[PDB]
Amino acid sequence: GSSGSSGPIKVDGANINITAAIYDEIQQEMKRAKVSQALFAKVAANKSQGWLCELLRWKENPSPENRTLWENLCTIRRFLNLPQHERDVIYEEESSGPSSG
Image (cartoon, rainbow, N blue to C red; front, side, top):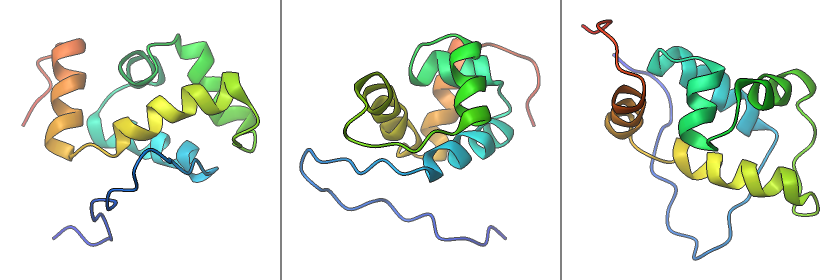
């Protein structure tokens, strides 16, 4: 069985709270979706692996002050909010692959 709190974040208007955790979620999401930093970053923020890899490397503290950061991290935050069935679809449609089962 799947143990862990994964409830849908109740609607909060148009105010997303980005936290350092965002980085962690990205790390697992990849292993969970079976994708790479390039893919997840290509379907999440549509950036290049390098842009993603770094995020996980430096893991700079996210804040509403940093645009280039907050902005991107904002789009990636909404992606993770999607249901497993969804994210899996985006990754698949984007980067096709036989690996499945």
